[PDB]
Image 1 (cartoon, rainbow, N blue to C red):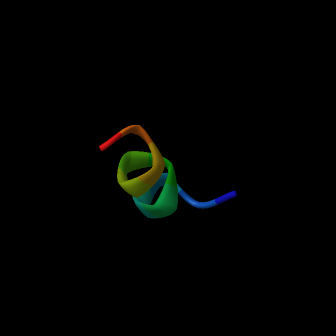
Image 2 (cartoon, one colour):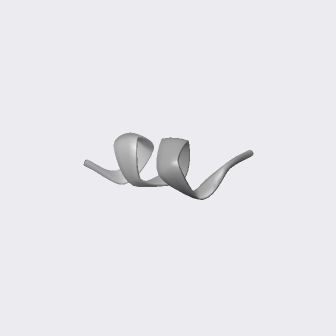
Image 3 (cartoon, rainbow, N blue to C red):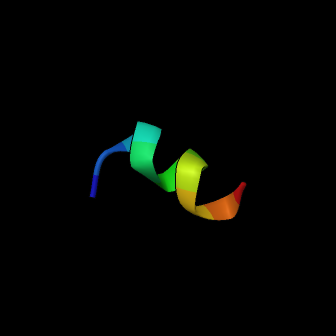
Length: 11
């Protein structure tokens, strides 16, 4: 949804 959570998700 936002770039930062996308990062969280892949991490």
